Image (cartoon, coloured by chain):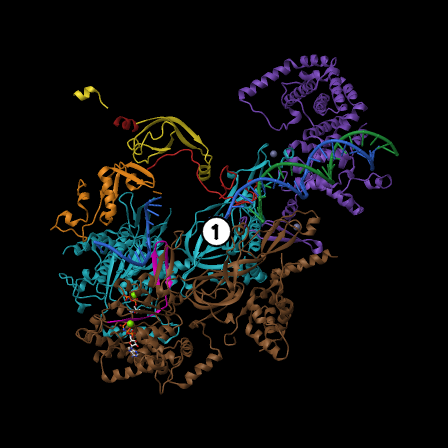
Chain colours: A cyan, B purple, C brown, D red, E orange, F yellow, G green, H blue
Amino acid sequence: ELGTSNLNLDARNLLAYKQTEDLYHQLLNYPQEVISIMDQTIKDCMVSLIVDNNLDYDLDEIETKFYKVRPYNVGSCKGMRELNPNDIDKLINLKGLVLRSTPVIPDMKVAFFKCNVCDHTMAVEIDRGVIQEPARCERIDCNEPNSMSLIHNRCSFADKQVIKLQETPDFVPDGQTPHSISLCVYDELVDSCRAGDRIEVTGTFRSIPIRANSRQRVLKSLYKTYVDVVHVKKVITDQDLAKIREVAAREDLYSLLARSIAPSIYELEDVKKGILLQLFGGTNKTFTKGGRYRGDINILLCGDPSTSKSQILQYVHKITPRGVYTSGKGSSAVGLTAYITLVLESGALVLSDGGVCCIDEFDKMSDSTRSVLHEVMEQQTISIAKAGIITTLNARSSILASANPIGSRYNPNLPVTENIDLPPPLLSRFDLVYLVLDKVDEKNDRELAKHLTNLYLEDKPEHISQDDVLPVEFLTMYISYAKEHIHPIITEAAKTELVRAYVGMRKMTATTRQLESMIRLAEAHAKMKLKNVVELEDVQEAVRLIRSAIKDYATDPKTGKIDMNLV
Amino acid sequence: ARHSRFGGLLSIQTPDKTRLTVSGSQALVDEKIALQKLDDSKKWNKRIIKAAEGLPNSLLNSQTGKAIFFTESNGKHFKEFINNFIDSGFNILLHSVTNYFTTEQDRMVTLEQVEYLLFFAWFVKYQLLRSKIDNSADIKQVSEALKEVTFILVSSLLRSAYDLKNWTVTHAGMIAFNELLNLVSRTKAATDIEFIVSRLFSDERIQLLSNLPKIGSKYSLQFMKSCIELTHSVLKVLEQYSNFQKVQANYMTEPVIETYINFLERFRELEDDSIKKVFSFFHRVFVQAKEQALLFRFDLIILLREMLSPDGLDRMSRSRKYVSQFSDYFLARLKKRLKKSPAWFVGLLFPPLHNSEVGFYQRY
Amino acid sequence: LPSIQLPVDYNNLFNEITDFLVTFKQGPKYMAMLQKVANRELNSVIIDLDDILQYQNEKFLQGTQADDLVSAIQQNANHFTELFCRAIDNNMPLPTKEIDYKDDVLDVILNQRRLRNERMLSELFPPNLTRRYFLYFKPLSQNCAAISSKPLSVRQIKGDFLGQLITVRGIITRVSDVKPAVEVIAYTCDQCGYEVFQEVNSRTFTPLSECTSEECSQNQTKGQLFMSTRASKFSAFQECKIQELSQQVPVGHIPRSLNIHVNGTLVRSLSPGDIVDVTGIFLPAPYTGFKALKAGLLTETYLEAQFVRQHKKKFASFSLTSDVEERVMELITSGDVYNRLAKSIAPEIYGNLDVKKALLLLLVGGVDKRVGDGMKIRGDINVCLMGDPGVAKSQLLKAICKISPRGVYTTGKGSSGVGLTAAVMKDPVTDEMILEGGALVLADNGICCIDEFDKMDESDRTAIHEVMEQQTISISKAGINTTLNARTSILAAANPLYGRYNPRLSPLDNINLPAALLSRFDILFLMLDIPSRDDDEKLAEHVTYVHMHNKQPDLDFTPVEPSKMREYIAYAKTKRPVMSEAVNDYVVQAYIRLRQDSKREMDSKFSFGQATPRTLLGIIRLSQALAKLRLADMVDIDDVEEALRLVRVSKESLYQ
Amino acid sequence: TQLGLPGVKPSNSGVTGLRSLGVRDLTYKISFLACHVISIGDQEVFLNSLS
Amino acid sequence: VVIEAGALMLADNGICCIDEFDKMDISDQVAIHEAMEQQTISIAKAGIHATLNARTSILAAANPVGGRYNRKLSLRGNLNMTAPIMSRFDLF
Amino acid sequence: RVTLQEAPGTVPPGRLPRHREVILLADLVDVSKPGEEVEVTGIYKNNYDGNLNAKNGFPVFATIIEANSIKRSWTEEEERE
DNA sequence: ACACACTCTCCAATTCTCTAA
DNA sequence: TTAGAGAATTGGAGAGTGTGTTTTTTTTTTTTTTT
Ligand SMILES: Nc1ncnc2c1ncn2[C@@H]1O[C@H](COP(=O)(O)OP(=O)(O)NP(=O)(O)O)[C@@H](O)[C@H]1O
Ligand SMILES: Nc1ncnc2c1ncn2[C@@H]1O[C@H](COP(=O)(O)OP(=O)(O)NP(=O)(O)O)[C@@H](O)[C@H]1O
Ligand SMILES: [Mg+2]
Ligand SMILES: [Mg+2]
Ligand SMILES: [Zn+2]
Ligand SMILES: [Zn+2]
């Protein structure tokens, strides 16, 4: 009734039903024959349903279609280096990360012949890669040799594509670099996957010979190997909606969500809150004219060493559906954006499109490399003009940055802008800037010491910082749904408060970007409550968080230094 | 469904535990296809044998299931020209040209013979068709063809052509003599015409017209088709004469049946109408005359599978009505015969056996 | 065309082989192995030449003559792999246990083919197709010893050795990934339903295309042949390269190298950067086809691997056989292992006992931790030595470089931050970009020694920051975007600012390291050269003795040798001792005092910076290392107070 | 190149067994065969152009 | 050389936009200067010679040195641009 | 042989210049020097080329110009003036 | 010298024709 | 009406011959000497 052709099948169901317990093993040992058997079973069953239940559907339509099974969840995954010559032509399962995909290649399936003298025609079937050309023209009165000929553009073809899969770092040997394997994919699955995707696959592990030269039938003794995929997987219900709506009604929701993104990290509540709002994001806007306005939030974490900044970046890197983690000394201008190779290739900010890009040791990279970020942060586009290539690419990428001040420990005898030491055109582009300080206090220190030492009372700890936190899976569901379905709008009340608040920060330095970032933060706060409107409460929270992040209340308003006693 | 290099391998085991190997994914499920694909690999074909030359392209040596194409003004102008020709000129032209050629037959050349026989044929047929369609037309316009002199002349051309083994004139003469008979059955469906029939069906001519399908087996596809259509007409007239049992037994024997099958197996090229004619004849041989033993021969049994399969004759053409209604009866009578006398299993491969003492029981 | 006599007849040696396989014992030794092969329990047979030598001696002492099979299979090793295989196939016993025979395609195919021949009647296939096992020779023990027992450097492998069985010593430079190689290929004929086989030895082959079978031919059946994987035979293949040690290269020359081939169960034994004693068969590689006609008489060559001996056992290779158990029981029963093991590090250096104890705890290291939400915490310990010239810093550092099974030594001036970590080189002629790991990757799961740490450039030292705490490397450059693993502990040495330590300034002025880097060392030891007529005399008497005798002076103390020391440390690195509440309270209370004292004295001449949270986990790591060395499963307060003492002593040099 | 082009020698797997190829292997590329192009990016002439 | 057209060729009889001009290398600012001087481009290498027309008007954006403008100083003091290039803008 | 290129004043805006190659025979060799602006009369001619056909994949012929002629003091009155 | 493309040649398998029982 | 003796036409088996093959940028990461 949906008019569709492919059926998923997790192989464990073959073990549950008694009559198919042995078919499960036969599937793994003989995939090419068994899968074909399954296909021709499904098609016949579909016909039987309409003819037995005597329904109105066209029998010819069902007879015309192809139906295919796609088995999955076959068994344990196998390490890419541990495939051996006794695995050839058996089913395999692999995990990995996608590097690149070649463009679609036409693959011939039926050949078309025409007689040069009498114009008789024949369609011929291709199997095992060889065209079975006729010896003589088959028309009775024109029984002549060498009389038929091939017509290329009246043949029939099919789509083939090759995907390059790389080994995940979890499996690499000690003191070595990851390897890769090539996947061949056909028809439905062709354009499914992009660079930087993370997937699990299922397919036959094949091997073939290769020729010594293009003139002759001489083969080499070593054989090429590859994988022939039949299924790909990425690594809703009314009950889910009921759970989401019920959770959204809790009073302690904002604190619950914030303390649950990084459960084992002690306090740092404002940092967690700001990161949560970066995860939700603002709203994307496009006009008929006057351009488009970014929904994404950029955050900078700056302060003393040992303060657990980099530990927080780990959580964000694993929570986000798409994203990258990298280091200041590890990155070049080309590697961060795009690379000429004549073809163009993607860098970190392009792979991270629609996600979060985590940059650590931000204070180590040079002014030359950091200057690349101005255009990408402001416009969310990358313009390129080099020999043989000139174009512009989209980069809807959120930056999360980590750095330590000049002198490597925060110096209270310098003003804040001089301790941070980024130039103003770049410091102006962050929505939130955090100061975090290693202030001594016996009350704080006893709690921190008890928290860290409690992790060593067990071999594999069950202990966790708080009684009530949400599981990562459900939290991901909440954030994803809220990003898709909710789109808040400005209320007149919110407009009045935003104008008032901006004039308050301005009249005394607040730039025009403080206004837009306030709007964006308020919108992010509204989504997190599943509201369709921005209200006064949301605007006031956006203002409060900005004032709290850069320690403004403790700042001397005239000299720009911070009184450490007030922290 | 899946691509050309996905394919597995299949093994098929016979009785006596011997095994064969075939490739491809459809062979896994369809044994009919596997059996056909198995034999299709084998290299040899027996090489083959081959009637007309010297004259311009025409109905005699081309497949005429291919028209030529008219503007509307041209269609109506051409129709007007030959319609006025027929209503005005035809009898006066034929009467002169025929009473010439009776005085000059010995001196003829092949072309003039093939012209005369394919001018006669065209105009007689076209008029029959035109008055079949409409009452404004009448058959009297072509009525010069029947009078006795022309009948003798078409007969004499066919006679002399057959004796000297000139096969092209024989072919054209076959076409002309077909139409004369067709026209006679028209006029009998309304005096002298019965006299003309009685003279047309003297014993000598029955010997000739019986002889003619037997030699057709060797020749081109049109020749056999002319033989069939002439035979259909020839028997149908003598059916409506009321002699008949003598004449029909004259037709029924192995070398005629051979021609009928040899023609029938090229059915992909033929019309819907010609197959109606062939099965009419098999109904005559098998049911009426009760000479069942002729058709128990294997290359007929192959044929009915090809033609009746989802391969060949369309699921809804009128042909399948006739064919399946024939084969049902065929196999019923075959079942009865084989269980009564098991020797026919080895009979079915070979021609019937002409010995006196065993052959009579064999045929019945 | 011509022919010669030679002293060897292979019939006699074949008879010796078949007697040896069924008679020798240390039931007979090799028949147990062949029973395991027959049961499908075992995939390879390793022949010991020490057995053949023993067998020859025993047969001689029984008063009978015998051929010297040991030299005979060293001189012409290639031929005897076939002789032993034929003998094994002849003498193979029947299975002891059920097998589930129907799992084998070749069994079904050959059974059906035999049945076809049986029906038709109312060598068949090459024997290589059914050899389920691999066979290798192991060279003579040098302590029994012959050339195969004596290692050669890659220069000494002249053209004389082609065909012989030899041993080679060197470093591996690169390793290929595994791919299949054909041995016997299988085909199917369509029309006559019959199967044929082809055997491949050369680097290339022509596949068959006509069914030349006599029955098929006599039926004039010119059928088509098609290839099949499902009944072909493959074997695993891998190729490597070995290169001579840099300290054996003669002056002004460039180092040489050899190509190594590996098949069967021996695959993925070698790894890059290993120092190893490979042994195998050295052979030529002939050309094929038209190339051979115009290649000339110069032959390419390579080494077939047979057996591999590593110089140092990696800690991951440990298992507690009773042979090792008996030796660790010596140390356990003797007692006071902490002091004995520390005193045993570099005995030729006088004094410095607390420094040696700290470096022993560096060799052991803390416990890796991974929390239920996905956070992970460093287990490795980092140490630094800061001191005056001429106090054996470089010497002690280079001594610890011998004990560790994986380790590298580097100096600050000779090193790039890139080459120290990982590099993106445009290395091939094809303009491809490839990543190649640096020193900190080669030291993965080991120690990295960095001398002259104060001479290295301030910008390049920042490359070490990520590796020190997170134990990983992250790169985003042209065409490459990946993370590597670097689970390495760093040991470094430096002189203070202005060279000799200056008492006019504070310790932090003399140290001259930034706060973020000074925090990443778990211990920084400060050692000063202060004259004393009494101590100088004792040191001089010790050193002069060592120069006189090549031995440390001893009256009471016997050091444990490095091998038994490695066994004890390797056994100790398996324990994972847990903390307890009584211990937790004590360390929690200690930490508060450290930060209060730091806050009080940030102004003071006795300042060393401020105690961060990374100083708490340093105490836990040192405590757990001490718990490992006493082979406990539980940290004790006795460990914590020692861990605090060892941190306190580092600063006492400031007080003369 | 893999076909019988006069004067030129022969040069992911293709198709084979065709007469002209012998033992060689043939592949293909996709391109577009257009039939017209239209772009979408003196005052008297200009005025005559306007409606 | 690959010859294929650059940005100034596509902007012939058009407006060419340069953003963050001050970040451009001196080695490339001089190329723009030479083109702007003549409204002409020249190629001579590898045995191939060519001359092309570049009747293009330039629109540029830049940052003052140190990120903020100094009212105490001339525009020349504030801007990281060489005097011959500065001399060829009609308006600032 | 000489390579001839469109003069820059003739080329339309926003387009690259085109090229052709000219063959000079017995009397015409060294009649012109690189960088000169020149005018040519001759036959326009073509021939088969295997490499063009191989690279483009269509039966495409190559073309050349065969030159027939090529083109680019004072009186007493001037001296007296 | 080693797979290929192409040419040449001879020999027997086949069908056609004539004669007599 | 069968069949057997003699003649003509065609197929492709297989033998032979000649042939071809080895083999100035432009962009981007890194070390080194030069102002
Ligand atoms: N509040 C905290 N909660 C949990 N762990 C903490 C906390 N404060 C410090 N730590 C621990 O102290 C260490 C901090 O390391 P790290 O994440 O690199 O901090 P950082 O801010 O990045 N310091 P640095 O890299 O020197 O600038 C880790 O072992 C943390 O587990
Ligand atoms: N306690 C000691 N016992 C034995 N030899 C010692 C001792 N102290 C110093 N030496 C000798 O001092 C010499 C120099 O040692 P070395 O390791 O090169 O010093 P260093 O600390 O690296 N000095 P430097 O590199 O200039 O900072 C060696 O020959 C040692 O034998
Ligand atoms: Mg950190
Ligand atoms: Mg030193
Ligand atoms: Zn044809
Ligand atoms: Zn065969």
Circle count: 1
Q: Residue visible at 70% across and 57% down?
A: C117
Q: Is residue A190 visible?
A: yes
| Residue at the extreme bottom of the image, as rendered | C555
Q: Is residue C236 left or right of residue B45?
A: left
How far from the left and from the top, in percent, is residue C292? 53, 52
Q: Amino acid type of disc 1? A: Val
How far from the left and from the top, in percent, is residue A340? 35, 49
Q: Is residue A513 left or right of residue A486?
A: left
Q: Is residue A519 left or right of residue C100?
A: left
How far from the left and from the top, in percent, is residue A270? 26, 64
Pointer 1 residue: A185
Q: Give the quadrant of residue A355.
A: bottom left
Extent of the magenta region: C473-495
Q: Is residue A403 visible?
A: no
Work out whether residue C32 or residue E92 is closer to the camera in this orientation and state it.
Answer: C32
Q: Give the answer, above or below, for where C398 lies relative to D14.
A: below
How far from the left and from the top, in percent, is residue C284? 52, 59
Residue C477 lies in the magenta-colored region: yes
- In the rendered image, the quadrant that contains the C terminus of chain A is bottom left
Q: Give the answer, above or below, for where A374 lies relative to C582.
A: above
